Amino acid sequence: EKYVVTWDMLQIHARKLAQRLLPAEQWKGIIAVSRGGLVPAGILARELGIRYVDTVCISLKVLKRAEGDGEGFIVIDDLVDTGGTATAIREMYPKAHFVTIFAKPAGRPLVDDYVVDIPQNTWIEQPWDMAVTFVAPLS
Amino acid sequence: EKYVVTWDMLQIHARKLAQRLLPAEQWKGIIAVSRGGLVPAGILARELGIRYVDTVCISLKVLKRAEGDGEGFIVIDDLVDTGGTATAIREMYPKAHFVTIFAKPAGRPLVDDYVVDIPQNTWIEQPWDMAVTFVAPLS
Amino acid sequence: EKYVVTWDMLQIHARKLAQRLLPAEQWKGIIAVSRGGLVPAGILARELGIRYVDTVCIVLKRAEGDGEGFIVIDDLVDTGGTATAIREMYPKAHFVTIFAKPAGRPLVDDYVVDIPQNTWIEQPWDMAVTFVAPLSGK
Amino acid sequence: EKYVVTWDMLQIHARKLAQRLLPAEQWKGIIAVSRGGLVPAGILARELGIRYVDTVCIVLKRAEGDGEGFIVIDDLVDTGGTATAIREMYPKAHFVTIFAKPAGRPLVDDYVVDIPQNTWIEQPWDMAVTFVAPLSGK
């Protein structure tokens, strides 16, 4: 099964998460989990008026990481699935508020907050993977 | 609580419903429940190659109705909520295959098929009610 | 070069048409030309508060009468063949389209967007968000 | 007249830029200019298969080094003030933007869409699908 995510709906969910993160003055910055958290981080940064945005990039190999234990930061990823990355991010940024747009059951309790529940066996098709394209009639 | 529906996602769900209605040759036509079923009916008509599209318009007042008992027709509405319209449509078109995009719990068993479950206390905001508009930052 | 219509652009055009059709109270209803008129009729029906929506399917099926007090809506007037049939059977309807090409534009009462006769046009119901492979597979 | 960028148009432009940046293998990473560069960087990172994405926040925070082997991306070069700071601290980066106005266009290595200096531009992260009352309340 597929769960399709359009740009406008990703933004609806990210703005709903931003509303939950008010007031903005409680936060020092946002750390995006690359790559999935980049677009959500841009939306949160806009809504919260936060210009201090950093990244964490992991494959376990750390390609690049934001310094510190996450105190006063939001850490955002697009999805928590099995929770592999999530377990590592908690360990690296134990004082951050860790949030995602989507959560599958296995990696629901590994984040502090998320917007939308997705079943475990469903592939989430994010809008950066798609284009509006002619489709032949199903007939 | 709100459930926002964009044009692209309405179309994703309607194309998924059309796939379930294959093969197209089993159907004589589509009857749209006005107004909500008009856009879904246009998408099904395109996907199934069906040019015989009619309407049923109810407020109980019948403004206009398609003739017959629905044999070989799909009857489509956008949502089944409490099931008021749905009870009347079954009664008027008892041989139709009655389908919706969305179903709330109260009016899930009043249709033959639907795509997406919506909680009873959630207002569905359809894309014909919205425009892409500047929004002030939440901050 | 393909002229691609998005859902949101179609709705912008249909709302511009709806504004011209005010006051809404003057209309008995809307007749959609199947299939291209169905989505534009849905938008007009929302904007004008009109629940009486019927269809004409070219004749497979038609709304009765001469069209007096009705809006008849299509997506596009191209060659004018459909338009010719609509003016014949609904001579007193207000016949409108979202898009018009020159060959057919004399046959409609109003349109929103004119396009060149040669335009290759695709409507939003012909397209969908679809996976596309990344430009690099690395 | 407002120049409104949709999400899907921004992605079309960013994919056109990504194609110019092939082969992807030549890059160490992407540096996003916060905040306007974050969404374009996400799209480039997908299209180019690049997981090393860093940020510069004007200095609140910066990616280290002189930029050699990096793409630096912003949404818009307007007056050129940010661009001036980026060429100073990342002189060996390939500095690109989606949109450019003339005042700033000499300061970037590449851009996709030029617009007039006076353009009132709104990006997709400034807008959202929002209820609007029907034109008739009937």
Image: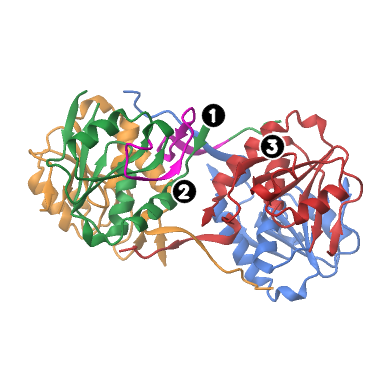
Chain colours: A red, B green, C orange, D blue
Counting from the top left corner in percent of width and height, residue C81 is at 16, 58
Q: Front-most of A108 and C49?
A: A108
Q: Nearer the viewer, mark 1 or mark 2?
A: 1
Q: Which chain carries label 2?
A: B
Q: Mark 1 lies on which chain?
A: B
Q: In the rendered image, which residue does mark 2 sit on?
A: B9
Report which quarter residue B63 is drawn in.
top left
Q: Quick check: can you spot residue D105? A: yes
Q: Residue B108, relative to residue A121: is it above or below?
A: above
Badge 1 crowding class, 10 Å Cα cut-off, few under 14, some 14 to 19, many 20 or more, is few
Q: In the rendered image, which residue does mark 3 sit on?
A: A47
Counting from the top left corner in percent of width and height, residue D123 is at 61, 46
The stretch of residues the image draws in magenta is B108-134
Which amino acid does the dot numbered 2 rest on? Answer: Met
Q: Residue B1 carries which label?
A: 1
Q: Nearer the viewer, mark 2 or mark 3?
A: 2
Which amino acid does the dot numbered 1 rest on? Answer: Glu
What SS does tag 3 mark? helix
Q: Front-most of B57 and D110?
A: B57
Q: Front-most of A35 and A101?
A: A101
Q: Residue C110, relative to residue A64: is it above or below?
A: above
What SS does tag 1 mark? loop
